[PDB]
Length: 327
DNA sequence: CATCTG
DNA sequence: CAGATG
Ligand code: NA
Ligand code: NA
Image (tube, rainbow, N blue to C red):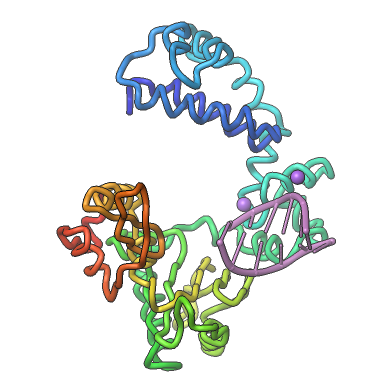
């Protein structure tokens, strides 16, 4: 956690580069397990040879740790932090919808700046385009102050379209977080579940509303279960307008809501730990359900849920208010 | 994993 | 359809 810091860190720096720059999924994938092992590792690695003793630990990595161990730097890391090429990938990518693959094509085409981009808006799909139009707005965090206004807006709409909808904004928002990255709504409807053969309108009808009232400013992708798009709180008495934000709406069968809703609430930690205990208690969990675990190794059969409360009970647990769902 | 691109 | 993004 702090003893093999630099090492894991350098490892991680490297891994990253293999994947983003190099297409180097393998290598990339390699730095990752090593970085992972030295991490758990209780000792203060004092050498490569020492480290190498580790699984995941090859010679190559041992060699780099050595150099690092020796010098507060690494040349290869040093070479990378310069390469306008390497740099231009990291940068581009930041653009929503720009992935690494693209980050390369773009560079090779000589597009390396945000300017480079606008310049060639033509060669960018709608996602990318929206992604560049609100580059600024998208990096900005989301104050809970705005969150609640946001929430309140959504909820008031959906209720309006159907008394029967059940929306829930998950996330850290949900956990108490003072600020958030994007808006995440969990969607449901009684009339829709596991077997229940569809109802697309179920997701659209709402997407529609939001635009009706203009909250949803743009669409990124919209499927019949998951929508990816833009929102914005109306600017008051003109002087201070909001920035644009990312939001996501998604249809969930009424029969695996709480499991999703529990799930998406995080934190990641609270999840596994919940899960690991869920395991003890003779159960299993995933994003969708809780299944009584056989002894034969495994088994299933979706235990019925009607709140995140049902789940706690199942695995016999202390119902946690989302707040403390930290770890 | 669900959507988009081409 | 593969392949890419989130
Ligand atoms: Na990106
Ligand atoms: Na392939």
